[PDB]
Length: 50
Length: 50
Image 1: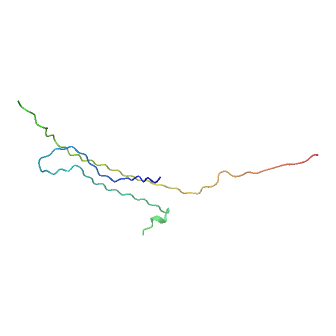
Image 2: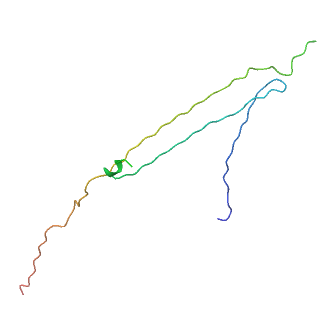
Image 3: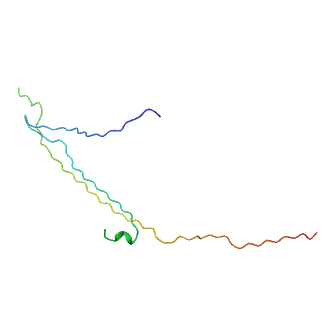
């Protein structure tokens, strides 16, 4: 109504590990490419080059 | 008189996960769409005998 409720962008990691003294350990990583393409055309004229 | 360790050093496991998805689609709508239900002929009669 007037009580705005927000959304969030979150990056969360909750891990149980064990290592030696002074060592660096990675607990999470991500690579995420995304692509989308949509085309609308006339039946025959849309395929003419350039 | 022997005592245990505070904890046991477990082995560490690395997990690599890959998710791949590809979507493709086509949509066509061509032709001529005519009417399929039209009015027909009519006939009426009226008379006063008396």
